Image 1: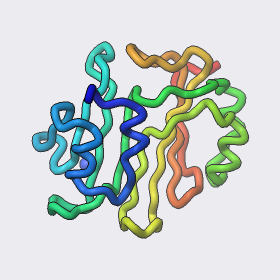
Image 2 (image 1 turned 180 degrees about the horizontal axis):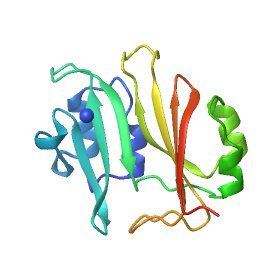
Image 3 (image 1 turned 90 degrees about the horizontal axis):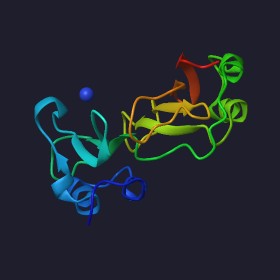
Image 4 (image 1 turned 90 degrees about the vertical axis):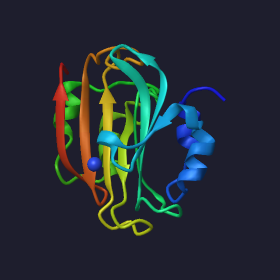
Length: 165
Ligand SMILES: [N+]
């Protein structure tokens, strides 16, 4: 029932088939083809330009293919955002995911994108986090203070911010 939600996103697991994903998300919410290729894109509540949404990628277009990629915008909210420019600057290329979260706060970041290129293997796993200052997150409009953090194999590779002080 209903649109795509953070709860349904959380319930979907790497390794699930397309049938299982569509059963959980609600097939009326979702589309494939065009620019998405074989990925499945599912819409949540309206949100300015567009909608919150999730995009799921699969090992192949086959019926038994497995979820190897999960991405979302505006479905999960950061729980306690405290990011500052100071914290952003003390994060460094080469830190582990655990040292980064300790630096920026457990509750400042949500998972933007998570992809296993050799699923079920964890080699080459790429993770992107989107992290916010105190009013930087919007579930409806433009963001107001955020960073993106890119990890490969568990280690920070890159960082970028917009509007942090
Ligand atoms: N892609």
